[PDB]
Amino acid sequence: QCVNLTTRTQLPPAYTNSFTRGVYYPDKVFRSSVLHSTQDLFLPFFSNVTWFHAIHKRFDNPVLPFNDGVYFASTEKSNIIRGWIFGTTLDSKTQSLLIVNNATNVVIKVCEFQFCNDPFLGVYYMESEFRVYSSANNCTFEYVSQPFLNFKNLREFVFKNIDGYFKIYSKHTPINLVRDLPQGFSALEPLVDLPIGINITRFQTLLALHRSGWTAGAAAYYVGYLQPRTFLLKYNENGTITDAVDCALDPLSE
Amino acid sequence: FQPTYGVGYQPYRVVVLSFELLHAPATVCGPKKSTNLVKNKCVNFNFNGLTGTGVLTESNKKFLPFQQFGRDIADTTDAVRDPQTLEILDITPCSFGGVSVITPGTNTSNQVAVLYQDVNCTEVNVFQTRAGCLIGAEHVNNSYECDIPIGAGICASYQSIIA
Amino acid sequence: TKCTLKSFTVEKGIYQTSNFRVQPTESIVRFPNITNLCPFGEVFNATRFASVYAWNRKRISNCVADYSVLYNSASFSTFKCYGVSPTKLNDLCFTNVYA
Amino acid sequence: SALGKLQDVVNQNAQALNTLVKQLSSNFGAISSVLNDILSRLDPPEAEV
Ligand SMILES: *[C@@H]1O[C@H](CO)[C@@H](O[C@@H]2O[C@H](CO)[C@@H](O)[C@H](O)[C@H]2NC(C)=O)[C@H](O)[C@H]1NC(C)=O
Ligand SMILES: *[C@@H]1O[C@H](CO)[C@@H](O)[C@H](O)[C@H]1NC(C)=O
Ligand SMILES: *[C@@H]1O[C@H](CO)[C@@H](O)[C@H](O)[C@H]1NC(C)=O
Ligand SMILES: *[C@@H]1O[C@H](CO)[C@@H](O)[C@H](O)[C@H]1NC(C)=O
Ligand SMILES: *[C@@H]1O[C@H](CO)[C@@H](O)[C@H](O)[C@H]1NC(C)=O
Ligand SMILES: *[C@@H]1O[C@H](CO)[C@@H](O)[C@H](O)[C@H]1NC(C)=O
Ligand SMILES: *[C@@H]1O[C@H](CO)[C@@H](O)[C@H](O)[C@H]1NC(C)=O
Ligand SMILES: *[C@@H]1O[C@H](CO)[C@@H](O)[C@H](O)[C@H]1NC(C)=O
Image (cartoon, rainbow over the protein chains, first blue to last red):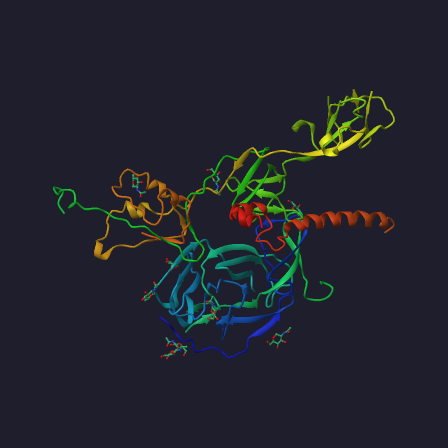
């Protein structure tokens, strides 16, 4: 089942500053009170991060190129964002990865979905509307896991697809800021190391409708892209990353 | 199918297991064998694919729950988490020290003493110095001029060999 | 010391000759608790099997399989492994199994 | 910075020792910087190289 949503308001996507966000733990190694230099796929400091809104009539679900890695930021309340879609052509010609969190449980599937042009979730005021794909023919991997999930929550995710291994780094932050990204430091802990082994070049996030036509709940998300660079990471006496230096930002940090 | 049938006409349940290996990451393996953890001994450890040789002792370093190994400045694994019981163990290298021989002239005597540098005396006329463990030299309370230098204010001489 | 200095006479002094290394005494191979075994009980001990024209296929994946509870089971009349040695199944790792 | 002359000597000695231990992590063009990985992964005719 697919439904075109035709009551959108045309508006260009916004842009804002990354500040010192997008940092994650590069490995599973404890380090204490030391400075460690790493050359990994990182998000640059103070970079141009793309801003999309869901407000009521704005309903931002475009389909974006994956590049070498994706930082996803979510200034979220009442859980509108439910999952993501990864693939190359997003049809049954290729094989695609689906990540959802509905009202009960977290589902990870690798199938050849015939995706809708406008896929979404829907909550009736209870969640009773599922329009993501019309078919699923050759499913090669299934994984059922724990629940991952004024704006009250900051949900930061980093997706990488290296050597057939799809790394999900995640962080949940209690925030109380109204509109933009908070300015601060928060290292992303590794959440899921996922054995898919497929080509991913394009992704699309999943929103949820509210029915009482449809209504979009208040949410905002941010898309940034990872590039290979070096950070100098600081590890405290408790082994928690508190600060980092982008070596290619300015000559002082160099 | 009747139960009164002979063998060869009776039903047979068949399961055919086909192990296929595509170049996606492999997730079907056998049972990983484990053995009892032995501490305070120089053993060859293999923890989750990280192998080495060391003495595994108890650690006061409190790891975060997603972290498994620990590295120093020189990127050598000196801390690790046991996967069976979530405890932290500080790997320490199986002890090494210089073996120095303190002797007078062979025209004088053939008696020698052995210095194990930076080595405790409990794991090797036995005397513990800051330079190391000295075996074969009688420690005296009297002070003389330094004849053969040992280090850290300790000197050896021949009169037997005294330190 | 005589062998180190290449002389049969050694002068008075301290001479570093060799190195004392403690040697390995055991092998310790601690691994995680053997959890999430593959559901072979729902395949082999199933109540209702299929017919051979419509044979059932279960894709055993994302789990760990103890093959030597099958090879040491007295019930099986025929156990023929063709491409692989039977006892080597607990060591080889495969991407997935089809039952 | 009154005692900087001693501190430079101490820092240079510690930095030289640190760089000497950092040189063990380089493979120098080989397949790995660990000897045990080479002894476990290869036959002796290539392992000697
Ligand atoms: C929602 O809109 C999209 C965009 O127009 C529709 O996708 C097209 O549907 C037509 C219908 O025959 C096809 O000819 C096009 O090839 C489709 N475009 C692409 C890129 O595949 C979609 O069908 C609409 N949804 C529904 C339920 O009608
Ligand atoms: C971000 O990009 C947009 C266009 O893509 C540009 O107009 C804007 O100035 C950029 N912001 C910064 C801080 O460079
Ligand atoms: C959520 O999705 C899973 C998998 O499709 C399904 O089993 C479950 O019933 C769904 N929950 C609801 C409330 O529909
Ligand atoms: C994929 O699905 C199509 C149709 O569902 C089928 O014809 C094809 O054989 C399948 N391929 C694989 C590898 O399963
Ligand atoms: C992955 O997909 C992109 C675009 O579809 C293509 O250019 C690239 O060659 C593909 N890579 C592999 C390994 O298939
Ligand atoms: C480290 O943890 C201790 C308690 O374990 C706490 O008192 C201290 O404030 C922490 N330091 C930092 C920098 O988080
Ligand atoms: C492994 O088992 C022991 C005892 O059976 C238990 O104490 C320990 O918590 C278990 N570890 C995990 C990760 O389940
Ligand atoms: C079936 O059940 C019996 C007895 O409970 C057991 O011995 C056998 O291993 C089972 N078969 C499986 C698990 O394949």
